[PDB]
Image (tube, rainbow, N blue to C red; front, side, top):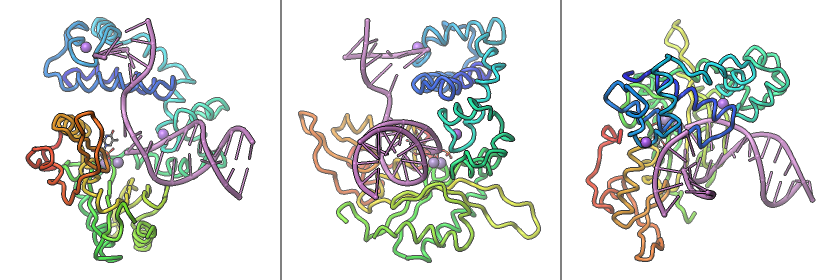
Length: 324
DNA sequence: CCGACGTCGCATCAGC
DNA sequence: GCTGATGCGA
DNA sequence: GTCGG
Ligand SMILES: Cc1cn([C@H]2C[C@H](O)[C@@H](COP(=O)(O)NP(=O)(O)OP(=O)(O)O)O2)c(=O)[nH]c1=O
Ligand SMILES: [Mn+2]
Ligand SMILES: [Mn+2]
Ligand code: NA
Ligand code: NA
C-alpha cells in the first residue's frame, strides 16, 4: 500500500481497457505496471522515478505525475461518471459475462444486477450461475475451509477408485492462508497419452451424490468447472458457494501439470526461462529437449515433480517457496 | 516503425 | 445436422 | 501501453 493510490489507479484503468475498450494488451500493460510498482519498496515521488521500472513507460509516468500533483486522473474521473462505461465494466464482474455480453446488455438498457435478475431468459447457463453466486464468487476461501474441502475431495475420489491420484494445486498447494478457488488435478494409471473417458464423469458424479458439488459451469471429458459448498455446521450460517475446477490429465503428463497449475505465475516463467537456457522446453504437458538448431525432440519421461527439476539441473523447490 | 504481448477446453454462435 | 468461429474463464 | 528487434 506504499503506492496504493497509484496501483489502485492503474488497476482501474486496466479494467476499463479490458471490459469497455476491449484492448486486452493494454489491460495486461496496466497490470504489469501495477505489479512492478506494487513491489517497489519506496513511496514514488515522480513519474520519472516510476519510469525506471520495467513496464512503466511515458504515458503511465505522465499519469503518475498528474495523480501525485492533483490526487486524481481526469480521464479516470470522467469514465467513472460515464453511466454506459461504468455499467459495462460492472456487469463483467458476473462470471460468464465478458466484455461482449456486457456491452450487449448495456446497449439494450440492462445495467445492473437487479436488471439481470429481471431478465433471466437472456442469460445462458453459466451467466445464471454467476448471477446467483455473485457475492459468493468474490469472497476468498480461508485455508481452514480449503482443508475441509480437500478432505471431502480426496475421500470421495479414493472411494470411486483407489487407484486415482488427486492433487489440490494452485495457491493452496503453495501454502497460502486463503485461496480464490479450488484447483484439483486428477489422473489414473489407465489414462496415458497413448490411450476410458468416464474417468472424470464418475468423480464429478460422486461429489454431486454427497452434495459437495452444487452446480456445473462446464464439463467435458477432461475438464470440469463448477460450484461446491461445505455442509453447514449444525444450525450455523451456511458456507459461501465456492468455485472448483477438476482437470483429468494423462499419467505421463500429470506432474508437468501439477508443476504448472501449482505456480505461481512468476515462478513458472522463471523456471521455463532456465529450462531453455539448459536446452529444454517446458509447457503444461511435457518437457522436451532442444537440438542445436532449436528443433524440439520427443517428450522426456516424467514420474514426479522433482524429475522435471533434475532434467534442468535445478534442485527441488518446495511449493511453499514458489512465489517466484 | 510496428508487431508481440498465455494458452486452450468447453459452450454457444454463425455459416453453410 | 456439421464445421469452424467466437466468447469466456483462468 | 510498453517493449525491442
Ligand atoms: C491463470 C494462470 C494460471 N497459471 C497456472 C499457474 C497459476 O499460479 C496457477 C493456478 O491458477 P489460479 O487458480 O488462477 N491462480 P492461484 O491458484 O495461484 O491463485 P488463487 O488462489 O486462484 O487466487 O495455474 C499460470 O501459470 N498463469 C496464469 O496466468
Ligand atoms: Mn487457484
Ligand atoms: Mn484456477
Ligand atoms: Na520503464
Ligand atoms: Na465476467
